[PDB]
Amino acid sequence: DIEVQDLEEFALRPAPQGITIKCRITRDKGMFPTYFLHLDREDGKKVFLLAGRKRNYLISVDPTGDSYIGKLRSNLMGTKFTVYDNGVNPQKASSSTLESGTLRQELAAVCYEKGPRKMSVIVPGMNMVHERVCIRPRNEHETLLARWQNKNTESIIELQNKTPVWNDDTESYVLNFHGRVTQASVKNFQIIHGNDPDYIVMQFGRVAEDVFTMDYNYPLCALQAFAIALSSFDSKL
Ligand SMILES: O=C(CO)COP(=O)(O)OC1[C@H](O)[C@H](O)[C@@H](OP(=O)(O)O)[C@H](OP(=O)(O)O)[C@H]1O
Image (cartoon, rainbow, N blue to C red; front, top):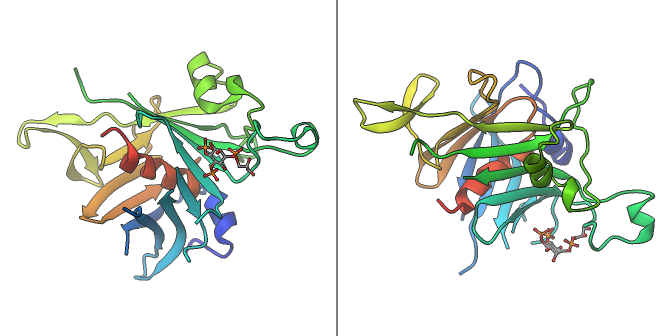
């Protein structure tokens, strides 16, 4: 019965050891769609966790604008995404902030590149106590996408979508969601680490017109996973 008291603290809290946090994203109720993330208690009740809405998507723990704990930035193309916390943008930072207290953190970055298409998820590395090693870029070469491209693999973690395999009976590339043949698309995917395709860090799939299921494990927290999933709504595909 994973505890959820402080919504902001929960949002930023990495998934525990051998525990999978299972959630459900529900879409809505010009003006942009509002996605709601709820914890799927295994006893039957839902616990609100986060609300995300395009305006860049602002992710907040307050459903009832511009107050947020997370922010999702996309490129013009919809192929490069970066998730920030609610800290100070280094470009607008004052001398006092820059070298005395601190700037905005980068919680995640996503890149949607014959075979099945690739999806790259870059997150902050974890320390020896298994807690995110805060990445607060003071410039362009310190971001998650820049480190990823420059191969500064030290404090980061390179994840990717699990490769779906062609199924002869379905005549479609498929993924296996808990044993069930699932049609691979930008709406149904799993995030793993190349070196270990058996460990599902994140599993996202649609279960209705406006309903999807999202499960996540270590090192991810609800804010990263939720933001990764929103990037799939906003992507080129
Ligand atoms: O520094 C402040 C933190 O206290 C706010 O950051 P700052 O980036 O300087 O000021 C903002 C810029 O116009 C930025 O381009 C926006 O999105 P982008 O970050 O995706 O490029 C950001 O949107 P918002 O983060 O509120 O959704 C704005 O607030």
